[PDB]
Amino acid sequence: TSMVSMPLYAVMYPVFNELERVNLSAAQTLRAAFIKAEKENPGLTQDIIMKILEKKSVEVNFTESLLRMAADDVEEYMIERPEPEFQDLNEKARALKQILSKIPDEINDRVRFLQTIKDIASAIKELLDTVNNVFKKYQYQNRRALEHQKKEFVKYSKSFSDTLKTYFKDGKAINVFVSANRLIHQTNLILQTFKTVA
Amino acid sequence: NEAETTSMVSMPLYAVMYPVFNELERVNLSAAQTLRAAFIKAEKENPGLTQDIIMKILEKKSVEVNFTESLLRMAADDVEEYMIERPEPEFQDLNEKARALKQILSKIPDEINDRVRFLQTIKDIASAIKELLDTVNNVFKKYQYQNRRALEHQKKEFVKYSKSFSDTLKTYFKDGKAINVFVSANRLIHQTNLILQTFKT
Image 1 (cartoon, each protein chain N blue to C red):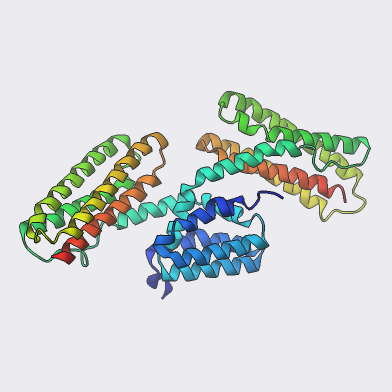
Image 2 (cartoon, chains in turn orange, blue; image 1 turned 180 degrees about the vertical axis):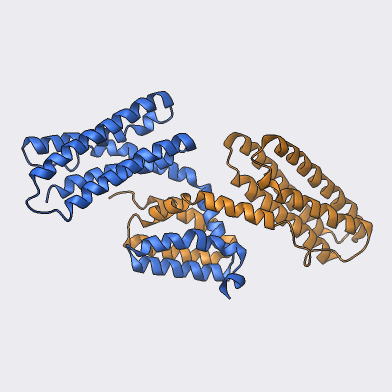
């Protein structure tokens, strides 16, 4: 007779529906749990959502932290081969991760942040050049996983750029931190794929 | 130890979800215990889950902005809801002053964006609140041959939320975020309603 439970279906469902490729079963188990809770307690899901939106500051402090942390895996992802193309891949990767990771501490000042975007674009570029320079060291009929990972990276670099544009109208910084983290993860995936096939 | 086993990515389970369940516990232990256990288990198997859930909730903020604004505008239909069907000047006053507060609060979405007319709106809300309160304390002293350990609570409860509304205005001029204002205005409409209910008993 009222719409007190709309947020269960309008927010929490889509939230669980859209996390299904991450972990199908947990999405299922948590939807079920909210539905049960909301059935007993009309209005509860709404209250929970509102308490989450109120911790925005915490959650942005945390996402900043995650992004700063994303800068440094040294032991796992790293190609073994001393070849210049492969070694150049490591250092161009590292430099991109480092620059992306420092976004939280440059974003609040327009000027130094304009320099950072340029540095980033420069780094993404320098990474692509090194990704393309290394293609030749893999049998040309055995590059399917390499070329596909390259596309993924570009897509996420497109997404990141499209995320910048939106930041200059919104002002909503988390979108940047989130997208830059995903980009960091994609350059990690480049390294994994590139080391694995070699 | 526990702090060292648990991934850094699991942090928003403890920084954000646990406080939510701790507050819910006071009002529904079962729901809280159950929702906590589901999060605990899901987080344990897929570290980072809670983080992803929260980010997706934050991304859907506009759905919540729309929903809260909606509830506020729809409250214009229920402005004459909860009138006390007692016919004496104290109660005629308490009905009209409560009706006028609900009417003005539900007008907020229309004024909020034009900041000039919003400053003019703030004064009237405070003026309507004060004129509700001034009417309350009269019916409080006249009709109190019965319940004190409930009516004292409600008068307190109204003041608590009313100054929390006023508080949200200043945070809004600091913020630019309407949802906080819509939310508190909705709450104050509810408190007003609770007042009309408490005096009916």
